[PDB]
Image (cartoon, rainbow, N blue to C red):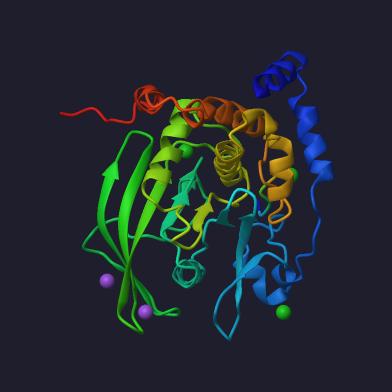
Amino acid sequence: EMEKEFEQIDKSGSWAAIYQDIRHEASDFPCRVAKLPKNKNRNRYRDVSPFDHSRIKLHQEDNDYINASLIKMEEAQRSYILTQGPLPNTCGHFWEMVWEQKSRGVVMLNRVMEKGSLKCAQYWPQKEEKEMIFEDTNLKLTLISEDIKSYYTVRQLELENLTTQETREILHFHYTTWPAFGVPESPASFLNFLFKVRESGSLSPEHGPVVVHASAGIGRSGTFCLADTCLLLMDKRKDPSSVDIKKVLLEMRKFRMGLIATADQLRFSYLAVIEGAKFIMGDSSVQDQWKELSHEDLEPA
Amino acid sequence: KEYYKV
Ligand SMILES: [Cl-]
Ligand SMILES: [Cl-]
Ligand SMILES: [Cl-]
Ligand code: NA
Ligand code: NA
């Protein structure tokens, strides 16, 4: 049934039209805090701001602003924090938020450098023996181990609140081949990654919301969260034909502007959910099929 | 240059 709508949209060639429909219908809420002059150097992009009503507040008295938004999906029963790629001066804020919000996973969908341009600060440590200290926020971050696959890397990090000496294990899911304003290689590559995030428990209600970012935190991350929410909805109602993807995206856009940055990203989200539905509808084998088609394993020596 | 969508 959702397939019918997709095929119909494909055959008619109106993805750009449906996408501009969404853009016109999208919530427009104020972003006053984000626009204050004292926050200018806390925003990566002038055209990407969190709404005042859903922004994450840092628990600090000096300045509580971080370019991050809480996407709370009541019906799906999941929350996500969508944020920009941290700036050199906001890496401390970023890990502060992770701590305060009790997040267990960070999903990164960009590379620090793309097309010879810096898109995100190196906010995590690359070598076990070179930990990072964020003094402004009294936090220490250490690389424990990493698992490098062909198009993504999972990293196990330890976050330490120096004040209380309490420590937490953060999982870092880094999608390394997803270009800005582009789409993943295949549905299998995207879904294999998504279900790796799910299998880690990072999305369990027993934790804070997962943090999802890219460079701006709306395009690739919007694609990621949209697909995950629709698949949750499909599992709860059990009826795939009930889930209206466009309605879900508009809901999400009440909490952060610009989610899904291209019509092709919108088209891909449909593809991903339709394919992912195979798992919802009870095909145990399909998860191994995604792993093969993703070619995640690297070549030995 | 300081805009996400150009
Ligand atoms: Cl100000
Ligand atoms: Cl590049
Ligand atoms: Cl938009
Ligand atoms: Na530590
Ligand atoms: Na503590």
Of residues A91 and A60, the one nearer the viewer is A60
Image location (x, y in percent) of residue A23? 79, 42
- Location of residue A154 with respect to A181 vertically, above or below: below
Q: Is residue A137 left or right of residue A157?
A: right
Q: How many marks?
A: 0
Residue A261 in the image: state x and y as whole percent: 67, 41
Residue name at image x 67 percent, y 77 percent = A38
* Residue most extreme to the left: A301
**Residue A169 visible (yes or no):** yes
Left or right relative to A96: residue A64 = right
- Image: A222 above or below A65: above
Residue A3 image position (x, y, % from top left): 65, 20
Residue B6 appears anywhere in the view: no
Give the residue displayed 51% in from the left and 68% down from the top: A90
Q: Quadrant of ligand 1?
A: bottom right
Query: Is A166 placed above or below A126 here?
Result: below
Task: Name the side, left or right, on which A253 lies relative to A180.
Answer: right
Q: Which image quadrant: the C terminus of chain A?
A: top left
* Closer to the camera in the image, A240 or A164: A240
Point out residue A255 in the picture as x, y percentages from the top left corner.
69, 56
**Depicted A273 relative to depicted A56: above or below:** above
Q: Assign the N terminus of chain A to one quadrant of the image.
A: top right
Which residue does the image show at 61% across and 64% down from the upper left? Answer: A67
Outermost residue toward the top? A11
